[PDB]
Length: 152
Length: 86
Ligand SMILES: [Zn+2]
Ligand SMILES: [Zn+2]
Ligand SMILES: [Zn+2]
Ligand SMILES: [Zn+2]
Image (cartoon, rainbow over the protein chains, first blue to last red):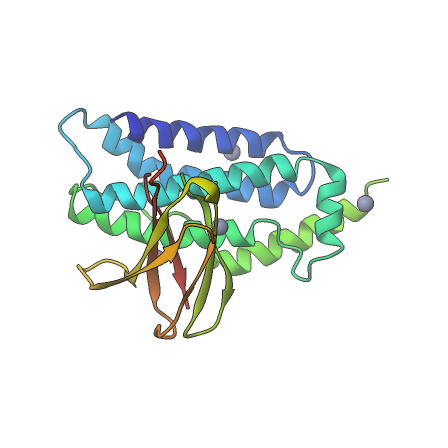
């Protein structure tokens, strides 16, 4: 109960902070919207009331998702500074900011989707379409690598 | 007590995990690892509290594993778990 709303609240704070970041916004708004897609089945589970109780396997998957949100939370404040992003863009090869966090959220989502449908009997919907998360990260990184170099 | 569990080095068959904790007060750790979901079996081994890294070997290439760390203290802990695919 309390842990369910804490993860939902933490996910909503992550999305709000991504909208406020000024540099490399395409990758930031991509991360915050992916977090919204993962917490929405948890919000619907919260809408049911006090009758739904997560099991041990579901709580373990939510804690791994919570630790990933706290990892992404530290990367948001870290990449809120211009010099920290330039230190990363000039030292990395793919120039993808949250490639480590996006991969951790992709594995925990398929573990949450399986447990939300089988155990809680909750209907879930896919996150996004268009392309894979790998191709979406490269397209957003190249667009951000172009606008960031234009800043004087 | 233990926090920030990551895979800092990885081969298709072996991993190297690392975590941050106050190792001065920690007796030892219990490292558990196994295939995720489906009531898959798990294997255990101990690591002294003075260190903050552990080596896991003998894994299958291309499998999503679940790695959990149980910190134990004798002077005075909730476990942390992550997921990694070799
Ligand atoms: Zn938004
Ligand atoms: Zn610069
Ligand atoms: Zn996994
Ligand atoms: Zn990580």
